[PDB]
Amino acid sequence: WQSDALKWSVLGLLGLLVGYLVVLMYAQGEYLFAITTLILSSAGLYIFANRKAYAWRYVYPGMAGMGLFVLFPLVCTIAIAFTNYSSTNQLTFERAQEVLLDRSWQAGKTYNFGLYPAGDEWQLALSDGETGKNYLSDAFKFGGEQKLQLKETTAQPEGERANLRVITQNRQALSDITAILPDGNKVMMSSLRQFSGTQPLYTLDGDGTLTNNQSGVKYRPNNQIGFYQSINWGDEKLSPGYTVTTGWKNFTRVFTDEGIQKPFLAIFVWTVVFSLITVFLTVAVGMVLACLVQWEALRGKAVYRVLLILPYAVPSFISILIFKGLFNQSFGEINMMLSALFGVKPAWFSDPTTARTMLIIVNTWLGYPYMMILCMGLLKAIPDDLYEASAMDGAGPFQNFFKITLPLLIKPLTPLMIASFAFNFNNFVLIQLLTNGGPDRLGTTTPAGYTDLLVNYTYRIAFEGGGGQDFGLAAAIATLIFLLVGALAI
Amino acid sequence: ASVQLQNVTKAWGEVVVSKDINLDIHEGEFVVFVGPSGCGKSTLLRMIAGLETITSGDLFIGEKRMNDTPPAERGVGMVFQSYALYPHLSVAENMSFGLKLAGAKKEVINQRVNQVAEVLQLAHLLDRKPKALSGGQRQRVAIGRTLVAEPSVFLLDEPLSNLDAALRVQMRIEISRLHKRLGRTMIYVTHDQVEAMTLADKIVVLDAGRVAQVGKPLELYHYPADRFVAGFIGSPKMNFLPVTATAIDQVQVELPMPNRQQVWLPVENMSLGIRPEHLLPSDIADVILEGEVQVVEQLGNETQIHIQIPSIRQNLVYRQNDVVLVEEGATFAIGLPPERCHLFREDGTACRRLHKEP
Amino acid sequence: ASVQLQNVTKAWGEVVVSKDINLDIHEGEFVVFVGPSGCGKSTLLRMIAGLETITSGDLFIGEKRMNDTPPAERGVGMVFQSYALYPHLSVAENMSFGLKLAGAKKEVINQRVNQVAEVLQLAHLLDRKPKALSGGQRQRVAIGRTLVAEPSVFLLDEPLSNLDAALRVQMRIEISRLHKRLGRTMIYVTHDQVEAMTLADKIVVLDAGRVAQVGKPLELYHYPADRFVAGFIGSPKMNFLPVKVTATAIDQVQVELPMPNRQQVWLPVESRDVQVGANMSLGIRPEHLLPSDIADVILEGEVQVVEQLGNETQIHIQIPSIRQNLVYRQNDVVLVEEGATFAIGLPPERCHLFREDGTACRRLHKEPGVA
Amino acid sequence: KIEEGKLVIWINGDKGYNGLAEVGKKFEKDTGIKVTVEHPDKLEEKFPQVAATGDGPDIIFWAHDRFGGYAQSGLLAEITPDKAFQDKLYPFTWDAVRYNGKLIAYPIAVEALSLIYNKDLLPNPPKTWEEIPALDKELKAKGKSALMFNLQEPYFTWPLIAADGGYAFKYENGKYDIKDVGVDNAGAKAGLTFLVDLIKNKHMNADTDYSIAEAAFNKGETAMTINGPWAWSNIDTSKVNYGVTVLPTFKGQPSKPFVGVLSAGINAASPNKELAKEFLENYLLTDEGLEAVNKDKPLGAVALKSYEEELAKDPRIAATMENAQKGEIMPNIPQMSAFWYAVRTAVINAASGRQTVDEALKDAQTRITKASAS
Amino acid sequence: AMVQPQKARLFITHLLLLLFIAAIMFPLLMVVAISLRQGNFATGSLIPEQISWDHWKLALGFSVEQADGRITPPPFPVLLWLWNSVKVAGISAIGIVALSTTCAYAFARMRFPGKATLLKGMLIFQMFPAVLSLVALYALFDRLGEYIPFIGLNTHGGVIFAYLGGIALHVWTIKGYFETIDSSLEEAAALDGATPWQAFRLVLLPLSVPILAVVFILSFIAAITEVPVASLLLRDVNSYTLAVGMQQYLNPQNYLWGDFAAAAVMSALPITIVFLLAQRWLVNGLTAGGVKG
Ligand SMILES: CCCCCC/C=C/CCCCCCCCCC(=O)O[C@H](COC(=O)CCCCCCCCCCCCCCC)COP(=O)(O)OC[C@@H](O)CO
Ligand SMILES: Nc1ncnc2c1ncn2[C@@H]1O[C@H](COP(=O)(O)OP(=O)(O)O)[C@@H](O)[C@H]1O
Ligand SMILES: Nc1ncnc2c1ncn2[C@@H]1O[C@H](COP(=O)(O)OP(=O)(O)O)[C@@H](O)[C@H]1O
Ligand SMILES: OC[C@H]1O[C@H](O[C@H]2[C@H](O)[C@@H](O)[C@@H](O)O[C@@H]2CO)[C@H](O)[C@@H](O)[C@@H]1O
Ligand code: BEF
Ligand code: BEF
Ligand SMILES: [Mg+2]
Ligand SMILES: [Mg+2]
């Protein structure tokens, strides 16, 4: 017997790693990650503590996984929809300020510089290219901010010019030196080869206002659009913009925008129909195949079984593209065969209906193994004596299938089918790679095509359409199509 | 339809579950299979169904070979030992399943379903699924499913085993009613002796996969061919005693009890057999057998008494009508009638009884 | 251990399959449940085992309320009506499964499995799975799994139903010997009237969700409390003839047979709540009718059915002005044809009498064997 | 936080990243600063995500068009080569790597489409597009065809469409006018008409795609094609005796392919800007540095004047640079998204005969103009 | 066991399967063709006119003597990619079986408040569009890495961990199946004194063995073919899975088709073996002889 003490021991031991890692998350700054990990671990311990929460012991590991990698992402995606997180507004405010404060402008002259040893101290040479004058400092030591008086010279320095290596090692201390020309100009290191009058483009006023030290123009945070705009607002706006909250703006933008709504309904219908036909054809093709391949009279079954899933064992990406080549209207071996036998050449990309047929053929090829494999397993739950009964009732194979096999499978297949509908609803990748959504829907102001799903036409708006990649718009649409497919599971 | 087997053998690889079985069942005959648990009753029945393969031998149904014909094409129907109900289907839907298959006529179906469910007292359960039924109720749905289909041959495997006594009585009757009205062949498996006796035109006794005997109910009861049948037909079991002179038309043997009485038997190291119902009160008979009472079972209608006799290893079971007040350890005496005695050879076979029974 | 039910109710929606049932099973008591198919015998066993919830009322085992205890913690073992064998494990493993869960030694496990298997005649089948067994073999496996477990309370739901007569006799004895060795509570459901009579210390008769009558075997056979019980215990069923009260004594009732002659007979039966002129039901068992040649009250009619059992003969008789045939049992092979004239005697001391509500006029004839 | 005192570089998997690592090994020998080169998958998408949080590589190598985006997002340092350094590179390349009038990356190589021809079928390659329908007729007699190219992607058809005044967005003077779009005008219609007419006359096929075009040139079935420097090694393996030359003229005017300039940008978040400047200016962008990468995997035409002039002794590279120079720099503005789809659709519509050239391009202009506005 | 009928039905089935198999094999035979074609060409004849072993050599570790004479070493470790794929997919799959089986058990056999909401929440929430997910995920494993570096960025641990959340559907699949099995087996088990855990392990699991193979297979496939998450988490070339590594062959203007195809064909091999192996758990009649009815 593994001790009864051993339980309250391991539970105390793990309940200690919790804290050691939680208060340790409270440090530096990881607060969202501390609150979240507290509720999750505490639920874990209590659940394994009192034997009244027994059943949860079985659910908790799985639900924890799900919350972590399914739920949490969903929450952020929704969260993002209430902000203008995009290509144009990608940085946090703090980061954008930090970028603007790293910006520089050349205020004065530029001098190539040299580093020369004087015993165990150093000497700094500058060379004024534009006058042919040369300057050299007194012997100094490295370390901290220091100012150096440079004097005009005609002589070479005594030391041998230092390496790039030596310049590099001393780059920190070197970058802290302010050199002063005879004529009163300050000059600091701007590269590994040059000292110059490089200066910070903006200064932080501390009340929020950034002011340009070249134009004199002034800028404040405008948290309405997420940019530094001039000052009461001016006409000029500084990039980079920052991410900022926009309430309902991305959700309305889909409802307010006449023109992105012209083909909505018509594309929606096609997506519903595409999903339904796919699910139907894949469940039906897969179920039959699974039935045939468990039939003990069928002597090739073990081999057939393997070969029938290969469309799922190869990654779909190459396959889709090979299908695109296969379906080429003038070339491509399908229409070259339909040329010979049957004498026709279907317009698989040019013609809306034949394109849709193509897409459904390809999808069924991709999706039948999945439904097959499920059925291969589900079919084992049907007891064999039910077919002895059916035999004694005068049943044939066809009758067996429809009165016993199909009704006994559709129940456990129902959730898998509803899910396959939702997945195929959003099957962005297939349409993009195969048809790009074409052929073209004529007169669509924001461009749409006949085989576009809802996802394909919508992400065209958010990610193409020329405004850069609008993550907020896309998140909001993702939520909207989610609340739509959720209401379609009615 | 008629059904006949011809040198039918059945092997599970090398375990023989049916050996050389030969049966002629004539159209309209009611045949019952009896035999010990695991002797091959359901296997035989399943071979007729086509749910099992015949290894060697011929099977014919209505004068045509069926070995190779599949179950669905034999014109047969079966009540399964384990019922084998459709779990997704209601009682009504289970019962109407066969009919729905071969020419569904809405009203015809409803009618024959309602009628059969009434005699099976299932009318209030028509809408339930099999999981919401009792064991006996499920057994009757299985029956209903086969009766409704009206096959050419009815196969019924222990179809009343989980019904109460009074309902069993009623079901036998209805099975009989239907056997006279349809005049189609019925093959019926049961462990109940009363059902075997009252239903059967023929009883086929089975032992470890081979046919021990075939005959009329009363034929097997009065005239069993061997020790096994004798001990299998009629319950309580026929008593056995290990029994010098041999007349030219009857046999004489000696009782093993230490007095060594000698008695004649109207027949052809023997075993003598006498049924508990055939033993007589002490005062009547010539041959008296006396020992100690071991077990007394009060059945209400009758009393059954087990008696340990000197030098006789096996207890002796006695049946006597009405409530007899006898107690364990008491002395009991009974009469051994010679004309009602059976006799069995060293191997097992019976010496044909010549006393004519009514 | 003791098992007690107090006002136990059970409902499936508005269907009530057990109504207010009260039972007091004492320790070591062998109690047989009987009743019509679908009355609640398994539902009771399942509520005791904890496999079905109790709607209302209280279950007590070993004196602790058990309604909310999990099955594993009841000390109950069961031989399911459906057997419910572990189909992925062999006979041996099925029978040794409960032991393996305890820290039982292999030799301890092997001893008491091989032992129980040889009395059940399963010895050669130890290796087979439940799919490679007959119905009667599977059933023995189910018995043998509970026998090895030796629980505090045995529940056996119809455990012999699929066995040949001879073997059924041997099993009855083994169950009986077991109950006498261990002296542990056994609750045993059966449809076989012999099993009931031979095994029971007490028989419970149920009728459509209610207890009809609890009693000793012979106490139920001789003195049924009501028409149902009377019609249920003993098979072939008790004959019933409508009769009229003509006169009453405190100790006896006089009735008029419904035949055209209107013969009168006194019965040794209580007259409590019996009025002259009322319609009663007279009961007489097939075993208890007498041959005509020596009888005071004769019923004669036309044979409808003959059943030749070997050991006896049962004769069904259509007697004028009674709808239901009379069933009569003669010892030995009586040669009679259908349609023939037949007469039997009706003995007043063995007649039962039931009021319009179906309740029994307590029989006052003292029948031997009931104390 | 990018780690101080070292250099992490990201470059695509089809560039000579092993070559670049030897340049980094030299840099380390001279400076003691370790250089690490990575080639992660989808680095063009990975960078914007790590760099925003102040992480990622110190230097990123990608085509210039993507750098206008990163720049806008606030992810690229403003680079400062002096006039002496800028003189070392072709001046048109410096136009490619500007955001808001400021330099944001170092041009490395130059990429554009050229005319590829079979010498054994066509010894003297035609200088004009109009010459081709005649030339296809004499090839059709011997079983071959003159010209097959990717008719499906606007990138491949735009050169002819552009020749006569077709353009994306007007490149005014450093600034791209978002409102001035040239896919509707006269020369666009003329370009696209000449193409449609080649299909109409069965010299070309409306559904010839990259794959089919390439396979026919490599099997010696078509005398010429239009394709980039990434195509040459297939042809080398095929052993087709082939030449790369200047794209044919349309109405006396040069084909205008799009120009892709491979460019190196410094992460705005890097603490190693000065180290990056030194590595890029004085180590990579030298004859010796660029030859290290080229030897690994060929760079094509490079922006370094001195090294281009030795690479150009190969006629193929010369041809590339020529077509580059006569072509259109790819605009580095977000609005190019809308351009691609609209134009790709318009060509397909006109080629497959669903729409006429006029309305097809009229519609494509409408789609870009209203996308770029609202 | 049953007496079989017409063997004209077998001939018609063999004929239809064969014709179906040729049809669904054709696209894959062209992938194989691309892998054996000299150069990198997405198109051409089923038997390539100019056959080449080079793509398979570089995938298998061999150096390639080319036209001018210089030897080309394999640019990538394709076989180690493949091994990294087996490991991530195998461990992943084991974890997804274990997590969803236990979960399905509670859903199928135990009762707890809001069980129904949870089950429908589970199916709903996994059906949200995965478009802004990788942003959330990176930010997650970046944080996690500094506390448990074994499951941080650039670790197989993290990738395996990332997949373990994808269980909702497998849960409903095993629940579904658990419900086809008669309660009375675990009821009997419970009266033998078996704990809910013991009933689960010793009775229900062995009878559920086929649906265990299904979820193992469906998970292994998902894991092997998976690109976005693995590619977002794995940095080091020598830790790449095969799906991530083969992305190197894809460039903006062209693909190394021959090498991509060889990679693609190679990735089907572990799917094929795992499928072959799992057949031993795909049996009929596991429950035969258990429950009369
Ligand atoms: C759009 C459809 C596309 C399908 C294309 C599939 C491509 C494969 C080519 C093969 C074509 C089918 C050929 C049929 C040949 C006869 C089959 C046969 O003769 O074999 C039967 C196999 O059954 C069986 O597949 C059952 C036989 C199937 C009959 C039903 C087919 C009807 C198709 C529509 C079904 C819709 C499903 C609805 C989904 C929601 C024998 O089974 P039985 O012993 O009676 O059953 C009991 C035992 O098996 C228990 O284990
Ligand atoms: N699949 C099998 N393999 C080996 N023996 C079996 C198999 N199935 C059944 N048996 C055995 O065959 C015998 C006859 O079975 P069955 O016909 O069911 O007996 P019963 O006479 O009780 O109906 C039994 O001993 C049984 O255990
Ligand atoms: N799940 C259920 N739902 C509703 N009724 C049921 C259910 N299970 C059984 N029953 C009914 O309960 C009654 C008693 O069942 P049961 O105890 O099995 O009968 P029996 O007395 O024959 O053992 C039966 O009439 C049956 O129809
Ligand atoms: O429905 C067609 C579809 O089938 C497959 O998609 C599966 C996927 O493999 C599973 O992991 C799960 O999420 O459900 C999907 C089906 O509902 C193919 O992977 C896919 O390419 C194809 O479009
Ligand atoms: F189980 Be009951 F007798 F139908
Ligand atoms: F066990 Be058998 F079915 F009599
Ligand atoms: Mg049987
Ligand atoms: Mg019951």
Image (cartoon, coloured by chain):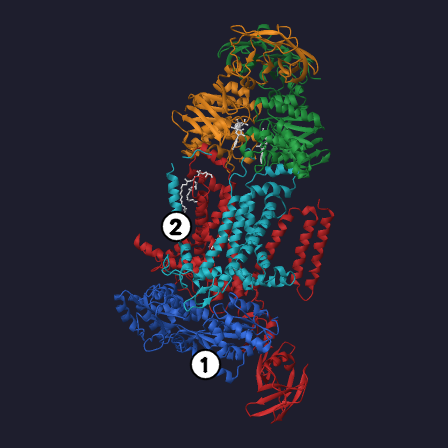
Chain colours: A red, B orange, C green, D blue, E cyan
Residue located beneath label 1 in the image: D305
Q: Amino acid at mark 1?
A: Lys
Residue A203: x percent and y percent?
Answer: 62, 80
Looking at the image, the residue that sits furthest to the front is E69
Chain to which the residue tagged by mark 1 belongs: D
Quarter of the rendering containing residue C228: top right
Where is residue D206, by image quadrant? bottom left
Q: Chain of mark 2?
A: E
- Do the residues at pointers 2 and 1 share their chain? no
Where is residue E47 drawn, in percent x and y?
37, 57
Where on the image, by quarter, is ligand 8?
top right
Name the mark on residue E22.
2
Locate the N terminus of chain B and report the quarter of the image it occupies.
top left
Q: Is residue C324 above or below residue A153?
A: above
What amino acid is found at the position of numbered circle 2 in the picture? Ala
Q: Nearer the viewer, residue B62 or B333?
A: B333
Please tell me how many numbered marks the rendered image carries.
2
Please, is residue B327 above or below residue E283 in the view?
A: above
Left or right of B167 on screen, residue B181: left
Helix, strand or loop status at disc 1: helix
Q: Which mark is residue C283?
A: none
x, y percentage for residue A262? 43, 62
Q: Which residue is depicted at the point 65% across and 29% down?
A: C115
